[PDB]
Length: 161
Ligand SMILES: [Cl-]
Ligand SMILES: [Mg+2]
Image (spheres, helix red, strand yellow):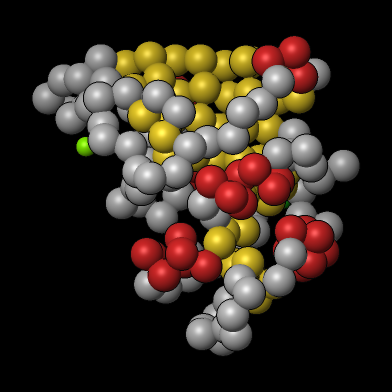
C-alpha cells in the first residue's frame, strides 16, 4: 500500500538537475503539501547524492550505489528492492535518483510529481517512457514567468490507474 512517487523536474523529456534537494516547484495552492513530505524517506542514486553532498535533514535518506557508502547519515542499498525494504512502513517514499533510477522504479511506482520547466536546459538523461493508459494526470497547474518566478512551469501529479 505504500505510495511510491517519482519526483522529477523535466525540460521536455530531459531530467533537470535542480538546485533544491527535492526536484519540484510547487504551486502556491499546493505548498501546504510540502509540510506533509518532510518525514518521508527519499531514495536516490549515487550521482544524485554526490551532487547534493549531504543528506536531506529529518528523514531517512536511502542511496542506491554499487560502491561502498561514503556517509553514515545515509542508508546504502545495492538495488531498488533493498531500497524499498529500507523504507519500511513509510506511507510514501520519494524517488529522485537519476534517469536510471526512475526507469528501474517505474513498474513499482504509483505516483509521479513532475515539474515541467520547458525553457530550462535539460541534463544528459531522459525520463523513462511510460504508458499513458496506465497513468492519470490528476492535477496539473501552469504558472507563467513573472517577478517571483524566473521560469514558467507546469506542476503535474500523475497516479496509476
Ligand atoms: Cl506519514
Ligand atoms: Mg533556470
